[PDB]
Image (cartoon, rainbow, N blue to C red; front, side, top):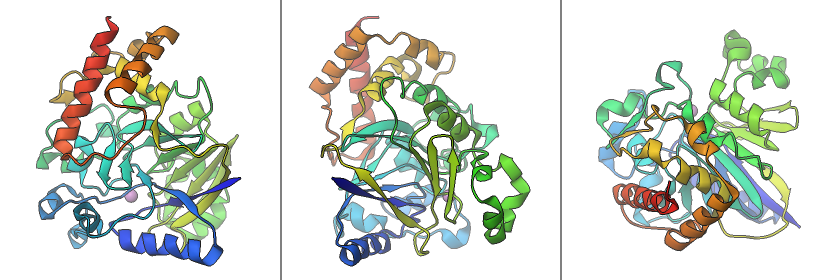
Length: 349
Ligand code: NI
């Protein structure tokens, strides 16, 4: 039994187009899409006011399609999981830094996380890399002054994600900019033929953060969407795929994977455990993480017994199924941290 998973590069607020194109796939091949994964520049602007948070050049200060979906005028026909890129309503994603549905059928993975679906474990790393900002905390609530920095990937995700392949493998990992160096691991000449501008960066092209995470977790697949081209490469056991932007034929591809089980979208248990155990570093809602704490030090405290109780409590308060919630995003931010804190404090440490 096989599951077909649509994989998409940059959406740029072309949601209706994306869906029509996925619809054409099912009509043209007779296959069913199990779900969709998108690697960024989602531009999930709820209303005109959010334009303030979209860092783009003036000619691209456009609302796009998302608000139709946010309003219920359109309805996404496939469960769509995504990470943030560099063109985002960054305020919305910060409210949802711990993940959340931006609307029915569209689930944001957060700054980073692992989820479960159909027997798969899927890791996500949002943003693009700029060294000047990799140790910057998030400040909350969102401020228009933060438009330039919110979408830069922080170094700390490396510590949050690095233990996630201890108990089983990672099937797919998602990022926006490419893992640094991976450009060298495919037919780069053929690529430079089409993207001569990529050539100056040499092996340094891409995110050192994503390089480390890939070298550490070694997922079956790593999927990325920043570059506006298709590209394939292999780094040991990992299949790298890059995808272009909606409107071009190299934007959408498909993974045909064994389906061992059909199972609703779920929080990953190891991820939940990391999330709870790192709470002390995230305890200040106005500014996090507090890196006077050591993330890996906090995660070193994980135990079999402790993990079990954590999952038990998560199941009690939040549930393992990731379910649609229509409260406003600022309400969700407070609600998810409330329970993370409550769980942590129930552990007694
Ligand atoms: Ni991008």
